[PDB]
């Protein structure tokens, strides 16, 4: 689902009227640059991620934005049915260390 | 969980700063009265319900508030992990007719 971000934003409990759709992070070349680039972003950011890459992305998010930054990770089970994990980046890293995630997800990250 | 409503409100995408915690509907005596009483409520309402009673409650909500009224039904999997079904009462009745629900839930109902 291409517009999976719409319900993710609603589920997130984060400011969602002003937001930056970022899509997928660069896997390699350009990735640190993109991350570095988002450090002063005050708007909610929305990213898509794969389940096997989520923990790395969340870890690096903690490194660049701080472990206390609010985040929401969501999986769309249907157009009306969503599953969501929300808290600090630190809480989500701990959560997705104990349990691997389950489908393509949307990450909704609080701005500065 | 007694304060399961807190994350349900966040997940709901409904106005959540002004809200009426209603708890459990009367099962029998007093139930129609309570429902009748909420008909002109403009604030979001929050209820707790059991999985075997949800469909009846949602059906009667449609009868009293209208099938187009926005609603969110949530299940707390942990303090940070929630599962949510949101749409019109009509959409949720259809959803919970095809699949019975899975634990104690919180219903977050849009006001008038």
Image (tube, coloured by chain):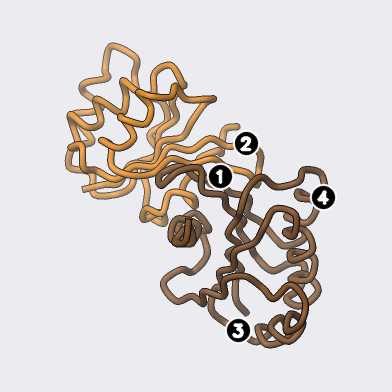
Chain colours: A brown, B orange
Q: Is residue A56 left or right of residue B72?
A: right
> In which quadrant will I find the C terminus of chain A?
bottom right
Which subunit holds the residue at mark 1?
A
Q: Residues within 10 Å of mark 1 (few under 14, many from 20)?
A: many
For image coordinates 76% across by 82% down, the residue present is A29
The residue that disc 2 covers is B77
A66 up-or-down from A71: above or below: below
Q: How much space separates mark 1 and mark 2, taking CA atoms?
A: 9 Å
Q: Residues within 10 Å of mark 4 (few under 14, many from 20)?
A: few
| Residue A19 at x, y percent in the picture | 48, 75
| Residue B67 at x, y percent in the picture | 20, 37
| SS for dot 4 | helix
Q: Are marks 1 and 2 in contact (CB under 8 Å)?
A: yes
Which subunit holds the residue at mark 4?
A
Question: In this rendering, do the residues under marks 1 and 2 share a single chain?
Answer: no
Q: How much space separates mark 1 and mark 3, taking CA atoms?
A: 26 Å
Name the residue nearer the viewer: A81 or B105. Answer: A81
The residue that disc 3 covers is A41
Q: In the drawing, what numbered circle is on residue A97?
A: 4
For image coordinates 63% across by 50% down, the residue present is A85
| Residue A52 at x, y percent in the picture | 75, 54
Count of marks placed on residues: 4
Tell me the mark number nearer the camera, choosing from 1 and 3: 1
| SS for dot 2 | loop
């Amino acid at each position: 689902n291409a517009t999976a971000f719409v319900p993710a934003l609603v589920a997130s409990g984060l400011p969602n009227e002003k937001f930056c759709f970022e899509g997928f992070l660069p896997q390699k070349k350009g990735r640190m640059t993109k991350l570095k680039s988002l450090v002063d972003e005050h708007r909610t950011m929305v990213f898509y991620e794969s389940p096997h890459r989520l923990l790395k992305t969340l870890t690096q998010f903690a490194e660049y934005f701080g472990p206390e930054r609010q985040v929401s990770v969501s999986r769309e089970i249907s157009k009306i049915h969503e599953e969501t994990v929300r808290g600090t980046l630190s809480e989500l890293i701990e959560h997705f260390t104990a349990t691997d995630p389950r489908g393509e997800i949307v990450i909704v990250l609080a701005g500065i």
